[PDB]
Amino acid sequence: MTEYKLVVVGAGGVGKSALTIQLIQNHFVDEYDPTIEDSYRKQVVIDGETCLLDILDTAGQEEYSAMRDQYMRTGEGFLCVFAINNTKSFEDIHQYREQIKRVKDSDDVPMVLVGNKCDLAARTVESRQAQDLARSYGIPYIETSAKTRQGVEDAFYTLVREIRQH
Amino acid sequence: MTEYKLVVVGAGGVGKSALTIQLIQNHFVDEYDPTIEDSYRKQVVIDGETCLLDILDTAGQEEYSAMRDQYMRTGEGFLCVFAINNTKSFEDIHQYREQIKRVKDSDDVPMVLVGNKCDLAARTVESRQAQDLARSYGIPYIETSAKTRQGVEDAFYTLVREIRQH
Ligand SMILES: Nc1nc2c(ncn2[C@@H]2O[C@H](COP(=O)(O)OP(=O)(O)NP(=O)(O)O)[C@@H](O)[C@H]2O)c(=O)[nH]1
Ligand SMILES: Nc1nc2c(ncn2[C@@H]2O[C@H](COP(=O)(O)OP(=O)(O)NP(=O)(O)O)[C@@H](O)[C@H]2O)c(=O)[nH]1
Ligand SMILES: [Mg+2]
Ligand SMILES: [Mg+2]
């Protein structure tokens, strides 16, 4: 069957693991548990197509650095995740974007910009500024909450549809 | 606030009204009630943007004909709906597509192809053939059921994101 190799990237603590576990296992994890590298494989049906989601959940820390090159080369699409209450994670998106473009030798890679933790009232990144950034990259912007499950299937399925139209 | 002028088109009986009422009023209508023309206006928040959805629900019958030109000219994005158990509704998509391109003087209009009634086991249009058609148009393909609410928010919100990136 068709397999889609998705990679979730972004700064430490933005909720990359919580979004992936909400999608795969249907629950919100709320504890401190830094990722090294986890993969999840799940057979699903998306718009009637039977497929397998092979998802790589990555570390937010640069002990990795050029160690990111390997997984970026094999990833077909990327969720670029920041937290709406963390301005530094939003500014860090530019560095993941440029690294992915450089390892894949391409200016248009299937990618979705995801603003997570949208359940929080202490917002520091306005949706309008993230939407402007996404518009300049030519990619979709989706807001999510791994805590309420808002936007979670939407972010992953929009990324599968982006790979489909590449 | 930002307003998005969406138009739902497709052959008679494919579920254009049932998809729109599931989104606006949260229930599945199951009765015979042919549309002449209905509009629905709803303030919503999509990816943190406060906006108003102005949705026009149209007639599946050609007593309309060139009477479609007016609403197609004012629509910013279109959901093109067929039913997965009705082959003629699928083939009719080409005629709505070409009319919209002709009235808007454009080869790329914000549009989503929606295969509705995906809860039914008596399928006559394979997802793969609809996905191929959507790929040739350069637009997203989404399967929906107004009966279970699967895919309903996804189809309308993907169309708002398509207007956003035009
Ligand atoms: N309120 C709220 N908290 C969230 C959300 N997503 C994640 N969190 C919380 O934020 C913390 C970090 O989440 P985690 O998934 O571990 O982040 P990560 O990006 O995977 N971290 P790392 O890069 O080190 O692997 C946890 O306490 C988690 O519960 C969300 O949508 N809402
Ligand atoms: N099982 C199933 N039936 C559906 C679905 N959507 C619509 N229907 C049914 O199909 C019939 C027609 O739906 P309706 O919304 O009136 O279609 P329409 O496209 O709006 N017709 P018209 O163009 O004449 O205005 C109704 O009996 C409705 O309940 C669906 O997803 N699943
Ligand atoms: Mg993690
Ligand atoms: Mg109707």
Image (spheres, coloured by chain):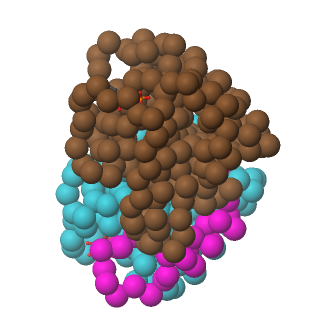
Chain colours: A brown, B cyan
- Residue B2 % position (x, y): 49, 28
As for residue B5 lying within the magenta part, the answer is no
Q: Is residue B119 left or right of residue B158?
A: left
Nearer to us in this view, B2 or A138: A138
Residue A12 versus residue A39 in the image, above or below? above
Q: Residue at x 33, y 37 (%)?
A: A18
- Residue A34 % position (x, y): 38, 29
- Residue A126 % position (x, y): 46, 17
As for residue B136 lying within the magenta part, the answer is yes
Nearer to us in this view, A166 or B133: A166
Q: Residue at x 45, y 35 (%)?
A: A36
- Residue B14 % position (x, y): 40, 73
Q: Is residue A156 visible?
A: no
**Quarter of the view holding residue A70:** top right
Residue B95 versus residue B73 in the image, above or below? below
**Quarter of the view holding residue B46:** top left
Q: Residue at x 62, y 27 (%)?
A: A65
Q: Is residue B76 left or right of residue B28?
A: right
Q: Is residue A59 visible?
A: yes
Count the numbered circles shown: 0
Nearer to us in this view, B80 or A125: A125
Write down the region rendered in magenta.
Answer: B109-138
Q: Quadrant of the C terminus of chain A?
A: bottom right
Q: Residue at x 35, y 73 (%)?
A: B117
Residue B90 versus residue B131 in the image, above or below? below
Nearer to us in this view, A123 or B73: A123
Residue B127 versus residue B156 in the image, above or below? below
